[PDB]
């Protein structure tokens, strides 16, 4: 009876196995745009993905991950609110059963159809596993998805999903360029938070872009054909794999823009 997104193992149950679920810096949150403070000391975000080396795509039973070779100084996030250099290890999405829900962060209570998370670890800690044990271990770049025009740079991901329908399937996915998933603007909100899935570790500097990307209805429909269950188990569609907004408690959200 492990954690998931259902009635009996979903977000409201996670605190039993992972008591940090009720902690002081949990994610996601609602971003109250009028209460976020513009911080003119915040630097432009530096996203340097020119040499990113995607290796593989994995259905892990909760989402799918596009994984990267993080053994060298390639695909890194710097600047913005960050001190030092953070290296890209994986990305994944959270999405809904319907276009009206699916994002984890919300903006003035608005839910987007999905949310992309580009996960990076602080190079001062040597690798991902050590970084997650530190309060400044990770930087997650979050990007909202709305349904409209297709995102051409997403299509390579969409097309491989048929080969990883089920928990534990992976496929070679070399040469995927995550620059094709980025909106025009790198204007952002930032706050200190957590992983949004168990173990819910409070190790993340969140950087949430203001500008959503548009994906087509057909693209997101293909996300919804994935399965939470393993092969030869009863079919439970992989939909609504998002954690709701958590209490802000004693945190300030900062805006890079006026
Ligand atoms: C399962 N896992 C690997 C992992 O990448 N976790 C993870 C990475 C990112 C996120 S999210 N949704 O906040 O961007 C959530 C979880 C893990 C991490 C730390 C300790 C133990 C397991
Ligand atoms: Zn995520």
Image (tube, rainbow, N blue to C red):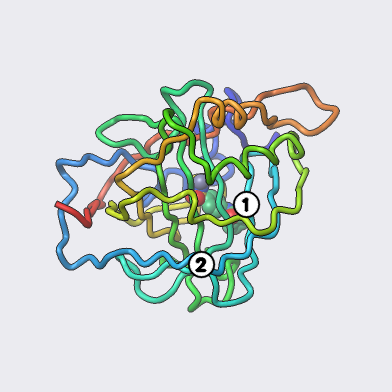
Q: How many marks?
A: 2
Label 1 sits on residue: 66
Q: Nearer the viewer, residue 51 or 227?
A: 51
Residue 74: x %, y % from top left = 55, 72
Residue 164: x %, y % from top left = 74, 39
Badge 1: residue crowd in 10 Å (few <14, some 14–19, many ≥20): many
Give the structural element (helix, strand or loop) at label 1.
strand
Indicate whether 38 appears above or below 77: above
Does the image show residue 19? no
Find residue 154 and report its image quarter: top right
Residue 125: x %, y % from top left = 52, 76
> Does ligand 1 reach within 8 Å of label 1's beta carbon?
no
User: What residue is drawn where x is 60% and y is 77%?
Assistant: 72
> Which labelled disc corresponds to residue 89?
none
Give the structural element (helix, strand or loop) at label 2.
loop
Residue 40: x %, y % from top left = 15, 63
Does the image show residue 126? yes
Quarter of the figure with the N terminus:
top right
* Mark whose residue sits in front, 1 or 2: 2
> Which labelled disc corresponds to residue 50?
2
């Amino acid at each position: 009876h492990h954690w998931g997104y259902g009635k009996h193992n979903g977000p409201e149950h996670w605190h039993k196995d992972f008591p940090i679920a009720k902690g002081e810096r949990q994610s996601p949150v609602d971003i109250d745009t009028h209460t976020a403070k513009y911080d003119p000391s915040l630097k432009p975000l530096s996203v340097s993905y020119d040499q990113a080396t995607s290796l593989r795509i994995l259905n892990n039973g909760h989402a799918f991950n596009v994984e990267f070779d993080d053994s060298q100084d390639k695909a890194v996030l710097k600047g913005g609110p960050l001190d030092g250099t953070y290296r890209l290890i994986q990305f994944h999405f959270h999405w809904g059963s319907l276009d009206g829900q699916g994002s984890e962060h919300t903006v003035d209570k608005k839910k987007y159809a999905a949310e992309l998370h580009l996960v990076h670890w602080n190079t001062k800690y040597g690798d991902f596993g050590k970084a997650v044990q530190q309060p400044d271990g990770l930087a997650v770049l979050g990007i909202f998805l709305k349904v409209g025009s297709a995102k051409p740079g997403l299509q390579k991901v969409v097309d491989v999903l048929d080969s990883i329908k089920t928990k534990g399937k992976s496929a070679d996915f070399t040469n995927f360029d995550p620059r094709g998933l980025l909106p025009e603007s790198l204007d952002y909100w930032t706050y200190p938070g957590s992983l949004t899935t168990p173990p819910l570790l409070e190790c993340v500097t969140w950087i949430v872009l203001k500008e959503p990307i548009s994906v087509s209805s057909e693209q997101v429909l293909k996300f919804r054909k994935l399965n939470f269950n393993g092969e030869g188990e009863p079919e439970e569609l992989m939909v609504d794999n998002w954690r709701p907004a958590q209490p802000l408690k004693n945190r300030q959200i900062k805006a890079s823009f006026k």
